[PDB]
Image: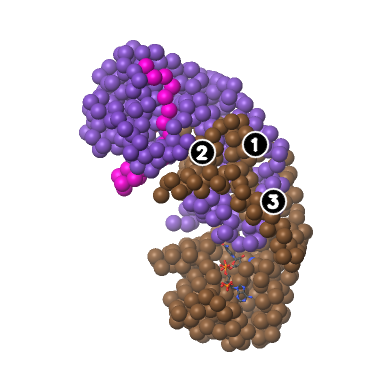
Chain colours: A purple, B brown
Amino acid sequence: VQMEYEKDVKVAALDGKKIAVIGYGSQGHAHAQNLRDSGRDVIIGVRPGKSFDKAKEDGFDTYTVAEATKLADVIMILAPDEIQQELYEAEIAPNLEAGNAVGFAHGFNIHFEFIKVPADVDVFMCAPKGPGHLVRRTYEEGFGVPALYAVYQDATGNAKNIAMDWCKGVGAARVGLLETTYKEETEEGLFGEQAVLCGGLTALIEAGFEVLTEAGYAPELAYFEVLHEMKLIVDLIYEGGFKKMRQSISNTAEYGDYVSGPRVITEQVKENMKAVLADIQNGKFANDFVNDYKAGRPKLTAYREQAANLEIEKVGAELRKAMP
Amino acid sequence: VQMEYEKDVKVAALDGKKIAVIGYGSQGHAHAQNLRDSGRDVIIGVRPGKSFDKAKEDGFDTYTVAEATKLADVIMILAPDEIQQELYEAEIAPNLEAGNAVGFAHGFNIHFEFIKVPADVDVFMCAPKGPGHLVRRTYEEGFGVPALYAVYQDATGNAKNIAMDWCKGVGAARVGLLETTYKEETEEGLFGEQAVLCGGLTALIEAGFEVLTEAGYAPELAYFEVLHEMKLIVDLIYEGGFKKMRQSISNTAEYGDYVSGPRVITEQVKENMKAVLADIQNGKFANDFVNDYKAGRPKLTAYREQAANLEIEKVGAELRKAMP
Ligand SMILES: NC(=O)c1ccc[n+]([C@@H]2O[C@H](COP(=O)([O-])OP(=O)(O)OC[C@H]3O[C@@H](n4cnc5c(N)ncnc54)[C@H](OP(=O)(O)O)[C@@H]3O)[C@@H](O)[C@H]2O)c1
Ligand SMILES: NC(=O)c1ccc[n+]([C@@H]2O[C@H](COP(=O)([O-])OP(=O)(O)OC[C@H]3O[C@@H](n4cnc5c(N)ncnc54)[C@H](OP(=O)(O)O)[C@@H]3O)[C@@H](O)[C@H]2O)c1
Ligand SMILES: [N+]
């Protein structure tokens, strides 16, 4: 297992395919525009609204989801996670034909089988390691965003070449591709964002800010010491790992890192992470997410309002405004 | 208090002061170069070596530490924390006169009283929220790095104006200043790097990587899901807090953030952080750091060799090499 590049995309499987991109938001605009600049035959299927208008004004032949699917050989579904299933059953599935291919940028609905694509139709994935605006901008500047690719079912024998050529067309093969499975992409992706990148990180910052402000330290200073200075730390890790970061910080900071990291993130925290992982693997989290959507997003509603009221967010907004 | 800027620097207290920067590392070079371009009389004092004539070659009147201190009104000490004390006793303290001012960029040795400056000499601090190369670069490009300032003892009545004019001369007043105390800067700064930015963060990432690889996931994919994509997340928080970050990530990632963050970082984790803070406040951590240095850094030595052997660091180095 090592990374693949344009030279490893040995068949241009998107040649002569009509491509429908379903949705025209962050990913949809990026995938469609990069593919068009790479010379592919791209149309957009999306509901009426600002995405429909933005696609038309960008010069794309723009249809309903149903009509775009009917016209297409390759259909990439970039609606939001919780919308895809209902949109697939009503608008996409009736308009598929044998030998088509359906793509996704994240494996959630296919892996947990909220969507089942018929067995004479390929299912592939190109999952860029970045948001849509970055996927577009790096492409325009001559490189790209690395990506995973996978195939869930291969009816034609062309599903993997289609997946890799998709990655090449959106610029990902310029920087690096990694093959995976739908299962691993979904479970590792959900785990990483929950336990480390998004959940773990924000909860860690928040706990540190609370300890400081509850001990009597000024919150403005606390904002700088647990959040603002994180960017320079993570930039160093991104470029050169823990080694480069620990070379840059003072020796006191470095010694404190080694000594106090393990006091905060303990074996028990690791066990907490294992419980997070288990609820991803057993479908509990997936059902919880979709059930919250079916109920009108009541849990997400309370979470989003509670987050808006956080002291660190209020202090941070005022500081970021006082700082060009 | 909120941020102060160039308009809040009431007195150009460095006017006609002879300024010695002690050390010519990343910070020493940045501080001395910026102050020179701002118009101040800067000389360097450092041990012989490539620092000594890096400075020689950049046109700085360079001297011993003893002789540069003898000549200066303002002496800013930018040597590493564990070196400052022996350097101060042997080389700086005998060459101070009443009415001088001694500066630091971090409060550790003054706050914990490993160094005690005579009561007829001011002690101030300018602590940029950035490393040397960034303090120099941003100044060259027209702005700067924000900074804290503080005064530990004010003999002349000019110590705060000296501190704030030092901020101004290195470019920090162009973007924002926050007054603090030596005690708060030291304690909050040690706490942040230990519990959140450095210690907590690398420990969290490593715990996530361990959970994934021990559950049978390939380390290469795990590296992307707990480390590589953190830069994009932290960049978003830096620009717009949790709110902007959570708008850009998918809806499953955002829901997973709210649900699983608190399962990983629990009340017990917060208690662990409180114990970290207590050992900063009571001097235990500071004495442990200084004592490790006096014993020949045996704890730091074992930490560093263990870190070089981490699986995430080996995998990361290979993947970063495969990604220009
Ligand atoms: N966020 C990330 O960083 C990231 C990274 C990798 C993969 N992904 C995955 O990419 C997919 C999400 O794509 P995205 O980020 O581009 O989402 P998005 O920015 O929120 O855009 C969603 C698009 O789908 C449209 N849409 C919503 N409901 C629709 C419906 N019934 N019928 C037709 N169109 C509809 C929306 O149109 P309107 O404007 O009218 O609402 C919009 O154009 C998910 O699978 C996600 O897991 C996300
Ligand atoms: N790391 C950060 O991002 C950061 C941020 C804010 C504040 N600070 C504080 O900045 C201070 C450290 O400065 P720094 O980052 O510039 O460290 P540095 O890059 O390692 O520079 C150390 C300088 O001091 C010299 N030096 C070492 N021992 C000496 C001795 N006995 N006599 C004379 N000179 C000696 C070194 O010369 P040689 O090259 O010959 O060794 C070198 O020029 C600390 O107080 C730190 O807490 C650091
Ligand atoms: N220091």
Q: Which residue is mark 1?
A: B264
- Over which residues does the magenta segment extend? A137-155
Q: Report the mark closest to the observer, 2 or 3.
A: 2
Q: Quadrant of ligand 3?
A: bottom right
Q: CA distance from mark 3 to mark 1?
A: 17 Å
Q: CA distance from mark 2 to mark 3?
A: 27 Å
Q: Which residue is mark 2?
A: B220
The answer to whether residue B305 shows anywhere in this view is yes
Is B107 left or right of B228, judged from the image as shown?
Answer: right
Judge by depth and name the residue closer to the eye, A107 or B17.
A107
Category of crowding for the residue at label 2, using alpha-carbon neighbours closer than 10 angstroms: few (below 14), some (14–19), many (at least 20): some
**Residue A260's disc number:** 3
- The answer to whether residue B52 is magenta is no
Amino acid carrying mark 1 in the image: Val
Above or below residue A244? Residue B314 is above
The answer to whether residue B21 shows anywhere in this view is no
Chain of the residue displaying label 1 = B
Judge by depth and name the residue closer to the eye, B245 or A88.
A88
Is A163 left or right of B227, judged from the image as shown?
Answer: left
